[PDB]
Amino acid sequence: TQQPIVTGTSVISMKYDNGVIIAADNLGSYGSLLRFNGVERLIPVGDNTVVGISGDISDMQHIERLLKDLVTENAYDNPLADAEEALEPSYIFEYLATVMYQRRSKMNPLWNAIIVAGVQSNGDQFLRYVNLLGVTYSSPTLATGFGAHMANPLLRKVVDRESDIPKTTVQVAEEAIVNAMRVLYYRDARSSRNFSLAIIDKNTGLTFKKNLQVENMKWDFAKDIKGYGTQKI
Amino acid sequence: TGYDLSNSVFSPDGRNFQVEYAVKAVENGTTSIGIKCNDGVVFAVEKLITSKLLVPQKNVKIQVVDRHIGCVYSGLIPDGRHLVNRGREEAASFKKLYKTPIPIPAFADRLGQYVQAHTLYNSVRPFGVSTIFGGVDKNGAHLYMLEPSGSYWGYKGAATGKGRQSAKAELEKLVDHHPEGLSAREAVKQAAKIIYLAHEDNKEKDFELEISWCSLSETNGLHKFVKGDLLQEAIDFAQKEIN
Image (cartoon, rainbow over all chains, first blue to last red; front, side, top):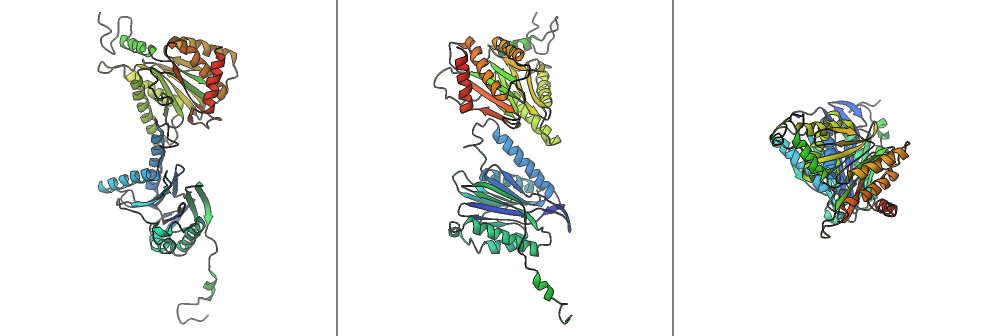
């Protein structure tokens, strides 16, 4: 991909005491045209990984096919494909990151930003980022695009350092994620009101909520805004 | 003379003797069977325990292709692994191009064309395996058997190995007695029975039973190995059925 066509906006995520949460809206934009709705940008892998992808949608579908074939291959000649030798979030990340950096180095990137989120076999929380440059980093909160500018400041007021992760409950984290989604719908011109949200909990497994909607929006004060300065009516 | 020294050479009868020698290599192997049920297929294989140093339940013999195909083979096991690798490549290619998982007849013909190509030149050796495979696709259940010559057909039941003859006899009995078709669990039980029966040709060594199945209702069209309680139930059925 040399320039993106159908694109998806921010993907937000954070860690909490027993797992991770990741969310993304269901919109595929075509420039300034909000062309496709119902576009699922969260790719669940196994019972312990969710991959949130933003950027070129065709490249995202290519990554979907890649993850599908990766699951199929790990199943081969693997009597423990559902137990000890099942796919881990770190495996899926490292694979995607290798691919991203190899495509960048071959001067033909996958025009994406990716957040892999899940729970390891030992219970640890995995949350890591990789983009079209091969850049990787990890933090208690992770967001792409506009989220990085708006979701992270909010989400970081809950988990500012590693020590805050045990203190954070799943309810607090999900509330923060939904509020950040509302803020993005307020201020991101390439966002949608409908979004999907995935929880990866080391006890309850993978919870996948689709067709969510931004609720409890404040719009009343708009009636009190007249003109742009001196106008009174 | 010397017509059997080089592969892909025609004898004056019109035969390829190297393929027949590969068939002998196949007949030297252990017994493996497949049974087509009402909504799926069942695969079973006997694994000789040469020594108790062998780890039980490990050394798995049945292989999976894509997520819906099961393959078992009798003969040179590494040749079977090579064939299964090629088949996995073929299925992956088919899915990547056409989105849908590869239909069972299509996969059968892929394997068959590969094995046949392995009889066209003197620079390659025929496969020393007979392969029973199949699964569930959009057109239902399919069971196939493929010979070292590249020949392959669809079967109600199939069997190869040293005990292939008694297995075929029992399969013909099962076919005659059940014109309506077997259920997946009944087919698993009958596969266990036929494996235990055909083991008598290797009676001097202990054997371990390995079963897998792909049923539209019991496994949701996916290939899964029969283990745990169902495997023990089939083992007990066979045990009290040999008496």
